Length: 50
Length: 480
Length: 50
Image (cartoon, rainbow over all chains, first blue to last red; front, top):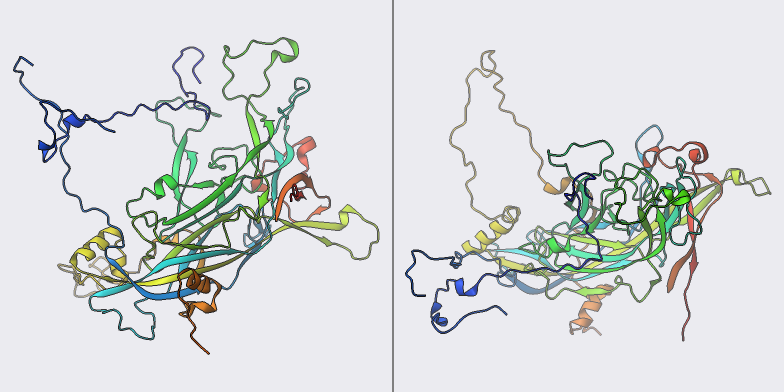
């Protein structure tokens, strides 16, 4: 639903037949401050989420 | 890196130690004392669509009783700290407190299976757009018709020690940036409310407020024409930190689109110019593109029945493992599979031997039948300082219902007491205060069930009692 | 026991309990008189199988 003069959407299209493709953003686990960080070397290893 | 640059970047630090929510298996100790409680038989007769009330008064002569309502029972258990046991030497009342736990539940239903039909005498319907022969003729004024529909089929049963929470779409207030014209679309908002006994279930038209969102008053059938159709908030009830509002639930739902209709009225938002090619002559004006289906819960079957079966609560979904805090339980029941509406009639004159329509007054009625049975275990909590803090933070009124707290009685510094309390220059010195309200659940309506006098210790004399004994091994009667 | 609703019908006869006036909006002309709000479905026990 957009105005006849402009094209700014006043009410978007939301139906039960659209793909809902979510893009999940995770925190960088190499930027986690672990109390015992000695569990992973930053000069030879890197972390990732599974 | 070959350069020494000034500062650093994000570091997600470990959070501060929080006092976590723990399972009731850690501070609530179970005992071998089980009790059977059950209601006599719960009947409710009324009108399926509206409450018949006096034309001049407002006393309700016949209440509204539909198969599409929420049955929220508020069970009352006897206080195990006041209960009379044959031997009270299993717990020490100086450092312990007792509470009932729910072990098994049987929600018995009584009437035969059947599907009831509801409809509006003036329903906002323009045409049947499922299979049209020619383009619609002139849409005049007041094109409403009398249409009926059988609703979506639904069964559910939520058990907890707090009242359930339902969701629906309501009317919010638009931000103060819009030039609001009359006849504008109401902005939507999802609202959470405590489901009370007598609220209408979602029926295939959405969980919405049909009073504030449809001023037409003619788009849904008579029973939900001015009601609020509510759907249980499972996302919110299972995500509550303590798990009190829901520690067991079932649900069965089914619906298909039976007929496909149109709406009548001024167009709110017209079809944009790039979604069609304009017509000429008959199709020069677009028909109403506001479609709506009539729901249909299909065959009701005896095998898809979730009621009349015992549920043994061994591991609750949340942290509250079936502990009925406050000596109180909440059984929510929807069952639209026994919603047959019996149609009665009465003869104005018993003389006439020829049928005349003006001789018989036709009424509709509906009857419900419930019979609730629970098996309750007896649990004791040894209230240390840590358990007392945990419980006072979980629910404030538990430690005040049960005589425990040792909190200061007066908690006061100084009170004023004018001499010559009868003078005229003392500014109304009456130290005589009234009393306020006490129960926070007074604003809601539940089907109150008083199981205070209904607790029994010999289970094998009750159907659910011997079902429990059978499922748990042991017999009970080494007699004869 | 199994059953579904095959046909949705109406009942004829003087209305015993009239629809409250706050449940609808009055009509004019053809719809000035309410149709019968007494509905009754036609049952149908579905397929029988061995």
